[PDB]
Amino acid sequence: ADKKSMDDQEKRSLAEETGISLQDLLLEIYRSIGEPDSLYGCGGGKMLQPITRLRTYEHEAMWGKALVTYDLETAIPSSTRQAGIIQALQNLGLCHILSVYLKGLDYENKDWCPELEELHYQAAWRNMQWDHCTSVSSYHESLYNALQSLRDSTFYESLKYARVKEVEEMCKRSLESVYSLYPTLSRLQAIGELESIGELFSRTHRQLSEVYIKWQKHSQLLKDSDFSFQEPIMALRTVILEILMEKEMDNSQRECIKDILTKHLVELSILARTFKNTQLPERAIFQIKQYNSVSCGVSEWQLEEAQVFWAKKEQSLALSILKQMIKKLDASCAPSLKLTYTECLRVCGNWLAETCLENPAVIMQTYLEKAVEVAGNSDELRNGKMKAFLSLARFSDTQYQRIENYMKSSEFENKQALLKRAKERYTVKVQRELELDELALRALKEDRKRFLCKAVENYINCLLSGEEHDMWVFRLCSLWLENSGVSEVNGMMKRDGMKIPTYKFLPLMYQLAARMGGGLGFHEVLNNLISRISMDHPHHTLFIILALANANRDEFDEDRTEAANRIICTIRSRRPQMVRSVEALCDAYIILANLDRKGINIPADQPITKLKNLEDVVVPTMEIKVDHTGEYGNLVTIQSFKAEFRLAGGVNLPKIIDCVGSDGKERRQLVKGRDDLRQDAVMQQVFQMCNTLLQRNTETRKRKLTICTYKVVPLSQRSGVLEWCTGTVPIGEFLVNNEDGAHKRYRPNDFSAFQCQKKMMFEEKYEVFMDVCQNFQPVFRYFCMEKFLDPAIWFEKRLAYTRSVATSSIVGYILGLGDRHVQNILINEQSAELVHIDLGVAFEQGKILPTPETVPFRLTRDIVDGMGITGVEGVFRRCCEKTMEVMRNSQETLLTIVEVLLYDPLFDWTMNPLKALYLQQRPEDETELHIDQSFNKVAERVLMRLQEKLKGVEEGTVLSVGGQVNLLIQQAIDPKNLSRLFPGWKAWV
Amino acid sequence: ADKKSMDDQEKRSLAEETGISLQDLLLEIYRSIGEPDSLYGCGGGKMLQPITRLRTYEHEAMWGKALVTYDLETAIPSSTRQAGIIQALQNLGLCHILSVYLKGLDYENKDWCPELEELHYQAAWRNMQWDHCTSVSSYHESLYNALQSLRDSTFYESLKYARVKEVEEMCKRSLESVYSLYPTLSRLQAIGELESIGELFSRTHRQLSEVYIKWQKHSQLLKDSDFSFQEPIMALRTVILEILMEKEMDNSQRECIKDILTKHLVELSILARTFKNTQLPERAIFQIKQYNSVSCGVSEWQLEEAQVFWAKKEQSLALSILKQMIKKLDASCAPSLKLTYTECLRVCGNWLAETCLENPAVIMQTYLEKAVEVAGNSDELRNGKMKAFLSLARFSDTQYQRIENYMKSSEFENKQALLKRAKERYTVKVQRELELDELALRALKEDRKRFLCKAVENYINCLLSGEEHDMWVFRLCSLWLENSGVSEVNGMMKRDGMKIPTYKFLPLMYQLAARMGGGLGFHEVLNNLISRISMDHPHHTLFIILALANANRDEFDEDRTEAANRIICTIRSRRPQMVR
């Protein structure tokens, strides 16, 4: 490619033949690679309708379309394959069908019986358990053998006879390039299950449960899964049941425990729900139905059919049956499965939430009845109870939110009603029901004081009841904030605040204190609890607590908070540590921060901070050091700080400051004044929470992507606490290397300055930009590639980097990101990764820019960097879709403290600030050349823009992302947007 | 029910046992009725997962789920039926599959071969045209017979031998409660097509086109349709092509005209698009592809694959191929199919609208190029030109609307920008680009004056170019109203107002006059045109015109309008009727 590119470059300079076939082959190599977006959308470029269309449809997981394609692929050769595909499709699709396809497999020709028989064996390995053994007129064949061989003994032998015969395939397997090794490993992992069997033919059932529990442990082990991979694993794990039914029919409890197997199968179906694939997931029920899970007294079977709520994609076929259960089962409810029933009721309520159909009162009956079923109420139940009290909250929250909307949203209506509050007359007319309207407004409050009250408890209850909603708690917290200082049930919430898993509760901290030091019965009481919380992992609590004052403290309005910070300092006095010498050290750091001016790598940190004031001797120490626990307080110290810290140049310059911990690990620290951290910072916490949310997406784990989080600290109101870590983008300097490097002989940064000298104008700028583009050739693909080595890495890391490049790249428009530059965003090939560093800009602050513009805004070279190919959205979007999906997934919870986010006392950043945002932070001092409600409204607008962002388009189209991506792509695309740029991204010029 | 209700009422007053089974039976009677919502959601109440779930899934048109259900319906008896269902599903679903299901129909048991063979015949009646005739080892069976009998002659006899043998079913049909009589009538209407054949075995091709055109007329006749019903109708109408391919391979133009048949098939696929059902609609392409509509120089075949834009539900697999066409075909474009190509370009623009992806400028290239392809430009084309100028309007309208939004919606942003209009200082700061912002606002206007202007013409052009957007015209009118009294291109629109199909233009009337009597160059000029329009079907125009004053007139502010109403009354004087 580079060769072709160079060749192209040469050909340009001059200004599989054409090798898109090679690219296809490379795609085929990308296929040979088999990397899913690199397969899918990064494999995108290949002009399918070849069977590539099928292969695409095959790349597509979707049997039917493929099956249709496979059907359409009657046109194509390898119809045997297409049949096998169809088989796979049938495998994907269905069974008696496949039996009919086994009938379809009559088929008269024996060659790919090598598949087909094995597939017939796989069909045995599917079904007709000992029957298809009779039908035997390969792993499957082995299984098929093993199948009857199961009916035994020397299956164990035969298993071995397969086992390495399998491993033979593994032996046969070569070049080590991918998983599906995994599938083999699965086919292996299969064998293990198969192997695992033999105890049974030997074999109590109680023990066997452990094996199920082991199979479950294996399933737990299989928490890492690919349904495709997992399919057999279950299928076997299921198929395990087959004679495990047959023989263990003998033992009733065993025949019973098949229920647990069914339950497992159900769980498998639950996993199928997880797999988010219909067919066996249905058939499972059928199987379950087919099973003695036909029997269905308590219909935990059907309780599974809560699958069918979305498993029939439509509920209410099901939800009716659920309702039927939720009647009949509730009627059947009319022992501990009562919890399940309650859970069912919760599920019913959930399904009723899923209903989103009858009165909240219906829920506030049925779900409140489900809540009464919750009142019908292990930790799982508690989790369920959380899941309930959460749903209970959530539902009430919904109602409350609806109420909140109906309050606040319909406050505008209530304004429209306040427009009618006394409308203008007749005293018999205007004045009367305003009392009721007040009572309504009271009811409106009382609705919150119903719902918001109830949920809060439920939230609290759920919050108490366990983990994983914590963001929604942060919303409930955000609610509790709206409640905080109000709604003395907040004090009751404070009274409920006994239940705080402060360890859980911790995250709020950066926000949490924002008001902590007004309302005594709340904020102080909260602050009290906060302090109480602060005590918990006070080490964790420290820096905010440290920041709490030290944000504003100076050795050279609502500071009652700062007073409360002293009152905290009393709690901090109550901390024996008196480690606040650290704060003094921070002040010494602030002094160090105060210190200032010979540009260079700079020795002589000595004068300041008492030369690191005993060199950061070990203490309640190791500041930067992000981790914390519920157990937290077993830690490391700071024990050295290397002085003479080479000055990191900057407007507020740092020194690269590496303080060697108790570990002596010396983390080069980013410290510069005139600096507000939390404004940047909690965005990280958000991004962290996002990453957590990302983490919260195993889909993101499936994406295997994440967010890049700077660890900084809120040192001073005007300064400073961070770690300047690694390898960041001096991309332009990298260009200044690489522009000087392979991009040598293109057009200067001066020409770019000449481009920057195009700042006058406007379409000419596009032309200029076009010229600038013509003047430039984003080599950055070549760039980190050069940085790259280990062509694995230089692919994979490159991919990873690309993935990395993509990885946050999604977040930005979602994020409402800051400025373009290798300064205004960074990347460490040190990290072999890109952490965009600005964290300046509010979501729309960039839109609020004079010379605003919009995109995730990777430049061409940044694209070229982002990927040297692929319309990398083809991956990146395909990746970033998940983000949107996750975003879409998270949206409400996403909003949740995201709501709280701009609600901060610190949130003037979230206000996209003034001084023209410091002259747009002196928007390069303009190239060194040239309403809280409204904020809330803007925030609402943001929230709208968020609601726009979160499932909305400009059209409200929202056109999940790929359109928005296409939009983003468009947003990325525009030479106009390019023309729309200013120096920071006119850098990108 | 009332009895039960009365019984209930009585039981209340007192205050299929329980007969929801009866209700189910009544549903089954509603089924016996067969009225779709009365079937479907009004049939809703019956507690399915019986095969009712299937029957529901069967009520559901959706093969796969049903097929899945049918698959799940391996559980159920009448698996033969479920198979037949599967067959129907396969019929709904697919073919080599059904062939595989014909393989699946190996199946060892002959009873519902009475279906299956007939279905195999229906599979013949599906496919393996003279081949499944060989596979014969019923309407379909008749067809299957007719199939080879087509290979002839006494098929015509055999047809009769079916024809009333069919009508026998009709005779057998009794109680007259529903269509599907229609399906029989279709199965009959089928026969007609089958009957219609015989001229061919006798048979020019030019004439035959009329029969296609007749089949099209029939299709026009089939404008009333149920895809379910229509399915065979097409399928036959398609299947008609089968030997119509085979024999008429002999005559090249005939072999060619199979393109028109393909075109018909394509139209059938278009109808399939209309049917809004994927499978054969795909297979059609495959068939088309399988056809000499494999050949694909101008890819009107692919121009159909604009199906695949949503026919692959996702475009851009296709739209890429479309783009590929819209490159390659546009490259191939680089004769009158140029209109189609333009239409394609329009479609491309439409697909580009469907893209909703790159710059409006991209459209304002590509679609404007499509508009240039529109400029590349019968009445259909004019309709297309409308469809273009409409899309052209619509796209611009979108842009203009976007502009309108970006104007008016972003007027709030422009208010947020007016908040920055002079923000508060530095005279080097606050004052500068407001001029550009004005120029932007100008550009914003100029955007409308690009888009709103362009669309308006396109709207006008489309408005001129024909019917059926008229509401969108009413929007363009509504736009023209925003334009009215403004945007002297409105006067140019008035100048364009020459094109008014006032008869079309009529509907606005109740609104239309609302301002008609301010801006002379517009409202009056409009009122003039309105009057001019009013002259058109002045009888229609009358009462509003009558109302125009008589709303307010009393024998016991902007009445310049009422004056204009008198000025209209002058035009009404210009009406000799003096019917006033």
Image (cartoon, coloured by chain):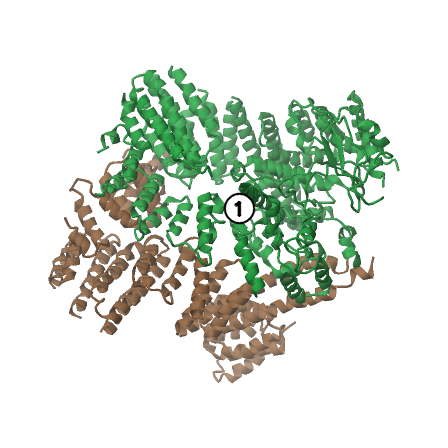
| Chain B pictured colour | brown
Q: Is residue B212 above or below residue A510?
A: below
Q: Is residue A319 visible?
A: no
- Name the amino acid type tagged 1: Glu
Which chain does green denote in the image? A
Q: Residue furthest top?
A: A204
Report the residue marked by disc 1: A881
- Where in the figure is residue A87, as x and y percent of width and height? 32, 41
Q: Residue at x 47, y 43 (%)?
A: A33
Q: Residue at x 58, y 41 (%)?
A: A892
Q: Chain of mark 1?
A: A
Q: Residue furthest right?
A: A556
- Where in the figure is residue B368, as x and y percent of width and height? 52, 69
Left or right, residue B156 beside residue A121: left
Q: Is residue A165 visible?
A: yes
From the viewer's side, name the closer residue of B322 and B452: B322
Classed neighbour count for the residue bearing mark 1: other residues with Cα under 10 Å, few (<14), some (14–19), many (≥20): many
Which image quadrant for residue A218? top left
From the viewer's side, name the closer residue of B182 and A696: A696
From the viewer's side, name the closer residue of A914 and B528: A914
- Where in the figure is residue A274, as x and y percent of width and height? 46, 35
